[PDB]
Image (cartoon, coloured by chain):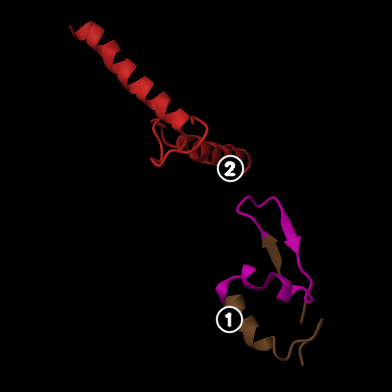
């Protein structure tokens, strides 16, 4: 998949790095575009990788 | 009786919140919003409000007449 996504506040202080494995943990926490692209690919998704 | 929340929401005039920067005023503004939200609903806030409003009314009435 790749490097993954990062979480931030409006504070620009704390950032939380996510692995490509743990995307499906945060789920809807990502922006609606990320969710719309992500949800269909959960069918073919594996732990680190997409088939 | 003064401990439990009355059906009316709040009795005490409280001014607006100032503009916020991420660091502190987020914490301060949030803490004030929560604490105010809890204490406004109580009957104790009711007696506070009536005391402020009516004793203020008398205070004006002593200069008025």
Residue B7, x across and y down, in percent: 40, 42
* Looking at the image, residue A29 lies above or below residue B39: below
Disc 1: CA contacts within 10 A as few (<14), some (14-19) or many (>=20) = few
Chain B, colour shown: red
Q: Which mark is residue A36?
A: 1
Pointer 1 indicates a residue of which chain?
Answer: A
Residue B9, x across and y down, in percent: 41, 41
Pointer 2 indicates a residue of which chain?
Answer: B
Chain A, colour shown: brown
Is A41 situated left or right of B62 in this image? Answer: right
Q: Quadrant of the C terminus of chain B?
A: top left
Say which residue label 2 marks.
B26
Residue A32, x across and y down, in percent: 56, 74
* Looking at the image, residue B23 lies above or below residue B61: below
- Kindly report the distance in space between the C-alpha atoms of the residues bearing marks 1 and 2: 32 Å
* Residue A12 magenta-highlighted: yes
Residue at horizontal 79 percent and vertical 71 percent from the top: A19
Q: Which residue is at the far right?
A: A48
* Looking at the image, residue A23 lies above or below residue A12: below
Q: Magenta stretch: give its range.
A: A8-32
Q: Which mark is residue B22?
A: none
């Amino acid at each position: 998949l790749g490097q993954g996504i990062r979480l931030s506040n409006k504070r620009k202080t704390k950032e939380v790095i996510i692995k490509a494995e743990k995307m499906g943990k945060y789920k809807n926490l990502m922006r609606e575009e990320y969710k719309n692209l992500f949800e269909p690919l959960e069918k073919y998704i594996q732990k680190d990788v997409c088939f | 009786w003064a401990i439990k929340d009355s059906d009316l929401t709040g009795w005490v005039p409280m001014a607006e919140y100032p503009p916020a920067d991420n660091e502190l005023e987020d914490y301060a503004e949030h803490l004030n919003k929560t604490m105010e939200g809890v204490l406004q609903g109580t009957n104790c806030a009711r007696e506070m409000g009536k005391c402020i409003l009516t004793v203020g009314a008398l205070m004006t009435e002593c200069r008025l007449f």
